[PDB]
Length: 49
Length: 49
Image 1 (spheres, rainbow over the protein chains, first blue to last red):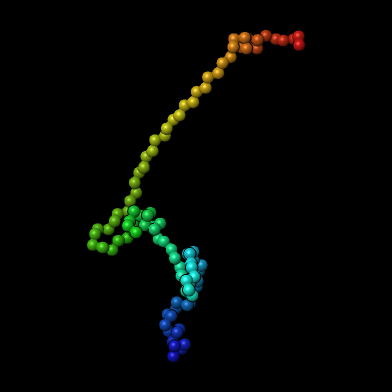
Image 2 (image 1 turned 90 degrees about the vertical axis):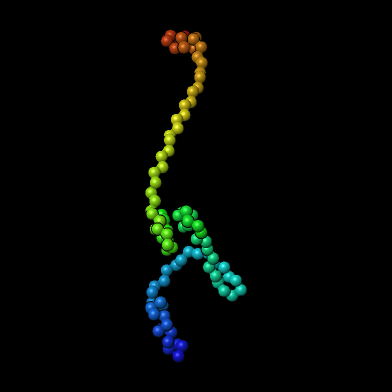
């Protein structure tokens, strides 16, 4: 059964504590989505984004 | 800082370089006048109003 097995699927993923994260989010239709750019780290290292 | 690479190329070496700048010097010069009479009467002692 799916409800009986959901603890087996998440092998300690729900156990770990959660922390707030900084990222821009938008509401498209019904989905909330996170949008971001990583170009800072690649500009810092002179590697091609 | 540098990024790790996984390709066949030799690993990118960490980079520390030395940057030397030069200090400029500026000079400023102002000219002022004082007439000889303006400087003479300072030595004299005034009593009458």
